[PDB]
Image (spheres, coloured by chain):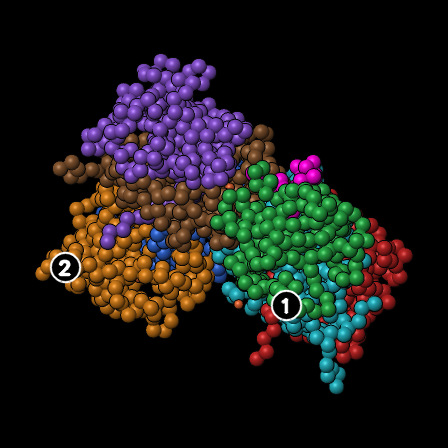
Chain colours: A green, B purple, C blue, D red, E brown, F cyan, G orange
Amino acid sequence: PIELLPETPSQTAGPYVHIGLALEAAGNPTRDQEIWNRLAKPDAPGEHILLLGQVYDGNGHLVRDSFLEVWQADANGEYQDAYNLENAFNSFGRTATTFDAGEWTLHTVKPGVVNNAAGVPMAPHINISLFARGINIHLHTRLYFDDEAQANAKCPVLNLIEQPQRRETLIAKRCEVDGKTAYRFDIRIQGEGETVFFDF
Amino acid sequence: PIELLPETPSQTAGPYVHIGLALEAAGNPTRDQEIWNRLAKPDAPGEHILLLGQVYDGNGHLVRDSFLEVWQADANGEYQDAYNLENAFNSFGRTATTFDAGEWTLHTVKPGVVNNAAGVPMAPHINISLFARGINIHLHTRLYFDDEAQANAKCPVLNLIEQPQRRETLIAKRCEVDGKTAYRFDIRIQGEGETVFFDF
Amino acid sequence: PIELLPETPSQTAGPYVHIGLALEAAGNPTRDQEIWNRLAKPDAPGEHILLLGQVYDGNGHLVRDSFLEVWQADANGEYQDAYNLENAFNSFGRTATTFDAGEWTLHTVKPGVVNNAAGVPMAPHINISLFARGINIHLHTRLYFDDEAQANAKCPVLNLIEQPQRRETLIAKRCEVDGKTAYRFDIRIQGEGETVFFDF
Amino acid sequence: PIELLPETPSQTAGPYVHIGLALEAAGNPTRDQEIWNRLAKPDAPGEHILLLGQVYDGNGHLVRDSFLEVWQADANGEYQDAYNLENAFNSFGRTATTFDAGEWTLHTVKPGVVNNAAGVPMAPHINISLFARGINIHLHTRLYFDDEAQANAKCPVLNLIEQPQRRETLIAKRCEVDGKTAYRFDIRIQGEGETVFFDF
Amino acid sequence: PAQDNSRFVIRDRNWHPKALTPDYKTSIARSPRQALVSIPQSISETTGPNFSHLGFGAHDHDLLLNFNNGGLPIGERIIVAGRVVDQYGKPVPNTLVEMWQANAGGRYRHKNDRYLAPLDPNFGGVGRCLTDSDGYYSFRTIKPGPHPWRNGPNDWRPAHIYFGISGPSIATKLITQLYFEGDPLIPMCPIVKSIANPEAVQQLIAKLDMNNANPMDCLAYRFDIVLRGQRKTHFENC
Amino acid sequence: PAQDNSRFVIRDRNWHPKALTPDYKTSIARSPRQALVSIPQSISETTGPNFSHLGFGAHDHDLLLNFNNGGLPIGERIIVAGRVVDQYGKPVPNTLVEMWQANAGGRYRHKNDRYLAPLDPNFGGVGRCLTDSDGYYSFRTIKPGPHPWRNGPNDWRPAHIYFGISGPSIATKLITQLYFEGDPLIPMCPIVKSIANPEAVQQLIAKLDMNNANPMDCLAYRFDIVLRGQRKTHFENC
Amino acid sequence: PAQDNSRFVIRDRNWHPKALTPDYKTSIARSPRQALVSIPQSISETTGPNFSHLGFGAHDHDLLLNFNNGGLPIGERIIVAGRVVDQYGKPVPNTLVEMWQANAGGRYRHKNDRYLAPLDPNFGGVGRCLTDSDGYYSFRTIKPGPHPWRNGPNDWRPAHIYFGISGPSIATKLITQLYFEGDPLIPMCPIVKSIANPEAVQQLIAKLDMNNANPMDCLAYRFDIVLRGQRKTHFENC
Ligand SMILES: [Fe+3]
Ligand SMILES: [Fe+3]
Ligand SMILES: [Fe+3]
Ligand SMILES: [Fe+3]
């Protein structure tokens, strides 16, 4: 058969990933421009939301060295790829769990609906990639919203998860943190309540 | 050493097994004669019973596409191998889980006692072979009866299972379905309460 | 793919074929029973006919060392495989061309119609196999009759010959020899008027 | 020595060529635009002519399944390569033998003179490529005109054919079809009167 | 009735695929985590159904004719034939061979298959027969097409026909899959690769069999099946 | 108009099949017995039609949709794609690629084909396209089935698609046949074997191309085509 | 009467010698130039004579005794024996095997042979027999000598015995030549070399068979013969 050049193989991001990719989180000096966890400035259109979560291993213990990358549509359902710190909104961000701060946070807006390649609407979601010591190739998942039950039930991506119980692992829980709208999204890498991870 | 011709290797029966082996269930027309789940005519000697069960994977979820073959002595402890739809009793039959509820059923008689090769009586049992998508080589088990506790305690096959707790997984529970004597035999392929599977 | 034992390869019957297979024609003593050119005794049912012919090479020169075997139905269209010199009719015979007698002859009856494997009638024919010096594997042909034009035009075997002109090479010419019905069938191995040869 | 990538090897166009390249002839519906045998609109400059011919195998039998491509200068000696069904003249066309009569036809104009690479005029000619079942790589030839005898005698391509007798095989015969000027160009693939075929 | 009068050579469960073969994703949750428990052969295991008295329809072995809704199925006409023997080379006569498959485009006639390739109105995809007195079986069918499935993101089964064989006892009964000589999907398939030993995989590849073809009609493939060796009992209980 | 401004590398007529290949029976009477006459390249041979202004229908390259009589054709959904380059490796853009084939069962939609395998009411078997500006072409179709033919008594063509490619001149134009990776009929076919060199035969075998497949939809095969090398003229007439 | 109930595996005409093998000079004018026409097997081709009731003389298989003119023939006393089977390995019982040969000096008992080596007054060179119920035949003879022939200017046939075998049908009937293990003339002979495949040539070389020799009496050679495989019809006319 036709064999292309093989992809460079993945390796773990290791225990010190934050020195390269999360400088403030590493407690190290930052450069003038950093890619971090504030996707939306106050002036961005849409519903401003705080996202937060913890990451657990297969023994139910906190992962205190994770690194997360996120990719989401703006409130209108458009992906904005022109990354610029001057923008009121960027579709891309980074966050982390650390020894001092085991709960990651993101400051963003709720994403609008995006159609799949067949033109079927997907429920509002944030794409997440998870990296850490012990993780040889990053884990892909999606954060959906518990206040989008009707859309979630019809999402062509959630519906590819064979078991309804596992679909529940991708639904973040609305709450309030310091008087602002928030959603909690915990990830369980292994075992009881294991978060669904995707391949694509 | 002496090496015979190797056996043809097993493969999974796949998710569409029912189109070759359970035609009614595939949603398809049947042939004049099918091998199915009614082992006994009403005139067959012995105690007429319903067997039923559900099959669970390692996550506790129903296996909705399983296919089961059974082999049992008649009420007089005789294996009837000359398969015929006109027989009062067939020792062989087939069943499959319903896709909605996942429950298989068999209509039969309670098997009589047969001896092992050393002449020791085995407790009344049904030999079962389980096939499905995800199962690369079929799983062998035995269904014994909870109202045969004295015979079960002395069965030379049950006593080959090292742990009493695991022996309990092979004991079907007497119940009533539509007011008729039945025994329920659930199979757990993996994990908590995992059913004993045999090699021979 | 599946490869069977290979067939023993053919070789030419050579210049002295008659010493083994045509003893009288070789001018050598015969044994008590010989397989020769009289398929029909006078008492055989059907139309008694003489067949005769010459064999030519690619330069139009007579082949004076050929050996021919023939296989034909009786007048009723039945093949008679129980070869016996006592029989009024045998379906099998042998003839030859020699230095002294360059024209072979056969004494037989006109064969009846035989259906092909699809049940379609073939025109009356004699199957011929031709052997000689210079012929590495024997050549198969058929002798049909010029007074069977309607049947010949419908024969499923003649109709597999793509060109009508080549079909004419298999049609023997009715004549009279010493006041008896005869057909002449010349074979041209190569070149102008080349006789159709079959593979099956 | 220097060895380039090898050319993809030819194979026969097969007996069903017409379904890909001569759709009308396959007995099939045509597409909106087809490349076919009318090279000239009525307004095309020059002398409008019909070309026709039959194709013979080595046994003198019609080749009923042949497919021909032609390439010729327009009346002004220009090769029109920008193929378009709206053009007054196309230098390229296609034709095929009818299955009953075996005769192909082309509607065109008489080509004007073009020079060879050394600047020597070639006599008016049509370049032809012949494809069919049994032809493993197409045969190239040229059709010249019998009323251009002076030009033909001086053509540097015709004079590369060593024997005058073979040059005659490329000379089409002026005739009249339905009262209109035509030239007949029969091709004999093999044997007596074998048509000259070129390599270049 | 049936009697206990033979023993069957123990299976090599490293020649068969193991239960847990995670690249075949559904096997992860449908594989036991505890060891199988070995038990000695008794009459329960060394006997099984014989199907000599099962009534077969005229076309049960002929998939070109057994789902006839006005025409022939579309696709590559093939005979699939072979012999069932045991590990000692002994033929297994009068044994039940069942087979099922997708159509020429890889679509199954099953309510749960929603692959976009169309059903064939004249193809059902199921056959059965008994081996003859010399151990040979024969079916006529259409070569199935490969078909995609929800495993990895671009996984495709090679062309395959499912087989079930009863044999002399419940100890010999087997389900397997037949693949076809040369199919470039075979080395890539995680279900084929559930079998760890490459020589075992070769045992599932049917060979083109021109000797068994009907000229101008259908091709043929040969698939021989080997069931566990059967021997008489010896020196037992003494 | 066209101008003479290039030369084409001379064909290797021992790499191509020869005319007389008697195991392919029809070649015996349809092969010249006289030698071909070599002639130098002139404008007549070094020019040819360009089809940039030919009007193509929307589905001309898509055999799953171009003979639509109410449904999809039955059989293995495949993309057949590749690149046309010359012997120097240069892409051949905006060139005409035509293809035709039998259906999934080896039956041709031609009045002269009476093979008993049925026609498919939604399959015609003809495609065309132009290569793009980088030399690439693409078709979507059904994998054709093998089919018997009246050569020897049990001869079968491997699965094959006929290709015609125009290229820059009448000197480059080619008809060939594409075969499929692993097909066990390839080594047995007298038409394949008209090509004497085994390495040349390999050039006609399309490779399975999983990278180009549409998951849950269709597989893909890659078939690259090499036309005669084209060079500028040099040192002529001096 | 005879019935059509079997089919015979198609011949490999590249395993057999081709018709035109010009180093064997007589083949040049005695080879058809048109292709053979393939036809399907019918009762005409799949039946043939059975010679069970042909009457054999007591010495028809024993060339040491069947031309007795007062003494034994001069030359190497040998048994020539073997089995006739078909390509599936099935024995061919009660089949007619005829053989003929030159004497110990390469001289044939035919008026057309004027080779200067003398005739042997007690040797005729002709044998026949039927294979037994297990497919075995046996002759006793003198090993034939090589002989010169008018092909090239110094051509010599290896020692050889001609064989004719009927088999079950006119489709199986064969004439061939047996050669002898080690004969240095075999690689040089243009008749042997009419067979293109060297493996096929090896099939014609009889092996010295000391196991079958009579001590102090005669040696023995083994020559097994394989006729076309015979199978039952299947799936015809449906
Ligand atoms: Fe490190
Ligand atoms: Fe499948
Ligand atoms: Fe000789
Ligand atoms: Fe074809």
Q: Do we see residue F144 in this rendering?
A: no
Q: CA distance from mark 2 to mark 1?
A: 103 Å
For mark 2, name the chain. Answer: G
Viewer-nearest of discs 2 and 1: 1
Q: Is residue D11 magenta?
A: no
- From the image, tell me which residue sits under label 1: A28
Q: Is residue A157 magenta?
A: yes
Question: From the viewer's perspective, is residue F91 above or below residue D156?
Answer: above
Position of residue A84 measured from the top left corner of the image (x, y, whole percent): 76, 62
The residue at the far bottom in this view is F238
Q: Residue at x 20, y 49 (%)?
A: G60
Q: Quick check: D38 left or right of A140?
A: right
Please tell me whether mark 1 sits on a helix, a strand or a loop.
loop
Q: Residue at x 59, y 54 (%)?
A: A102
Label 2 with label 1: CB-CB less than 8 Å:
no
Q: Quadrant of residue E72?
A: top right
**Residues in magenta, as a range:** A143-163
Q: Residue at x 61, y 66 (%)?
A: A19
Position of residue D37 measured from the top left corner of the image (x, y, whole percent): 77, 54
Amino acid type at image mark 2: Cys
Q: Quick check: E230 left or right of A43?
A: left
**Can you tell which mark lies on residue G79?**
none
Position of residue B56 measured from the top left corner of the image (x, y, whole percent): 46, 35
Q: Do we see residue F16 in this rendering?
A: yes
Q: Is disc 1 surrounded by few (<14), some (14 to 19) or many (20+) residues within 10 Å?
A: few
For mark 1, name the chain. Answer: A
Residue placed most toward the observer, E135 or A149? A149
Q: Quick check: G101 left or right of C184?
A: left
Q: Residue at x 34, y 73 (%)?
A: G154
Amino acid type at image mark 1: Asn
- From the image, tell me which residue sits under label 2: G218
